[PDB]
Image 1 (spheres, helix red, strand yellow):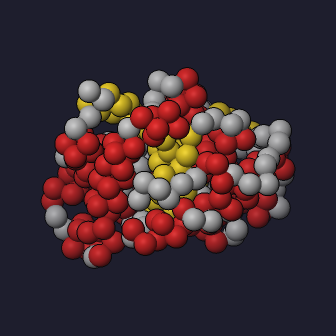
Image 2 (spheres, one colour):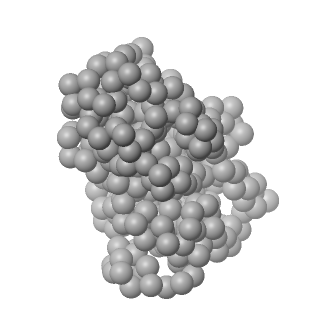
Length: 298
């Protein structure tokens, strides 16, 4: 008997159909505990403790984990982040210089923390000119409702909740264009991968398979009611918001997975770690993170 705990996050993307349908459990024959986490930093801690074996991480938390030598490897990409992650602000903030003096929340070391710092750099604004506060997404929504923050860089469901009364100042498709792309990845602990390689392969298959019908024709996929309902439920967003959110990333074919996992991801980690080091968020970065990536499960 195999028991596996999977740490998931709230991005509305096509692999959530497989989560909703329990495909991973059914194909692997494992008993699967799905645990929702607020952001990637707490997932890194759970992977390090061994309380989670498979987790969804942003590229920024991954780079922090790898710089700490956590025994995990990226074994597939979940998505390339675009405008599904965005900086939403009070509508009185209309231009980047209007951020100066404002209180802006991010979950610390998240992709949205990373992207906010990249955006400020692009705009010529020093991070210390903004009151950047660490809040988890639920606390961000609550502080927004109270007017205790002026804006936040967030993913669903916080992004679309704030967007109802706020304005999008930038997003991760733009930030990516500016030279600071972010990704979401799936990672696995070495000891789990060693003991249950077939189960890891089953996880990868379930996710990749679920994404292919979307990639083949996004519009047709989004008009299947069941696809929308499953994402709405797991992400915690209105059905009406799901298509916008799903189109706010790009996903990979199996050929693209193998290609990305054989070089590009390693470079992405190096670049991410380096930017974090410059911004004072990690003490040291390696010139190679090949230990933290594999194509062997796809």
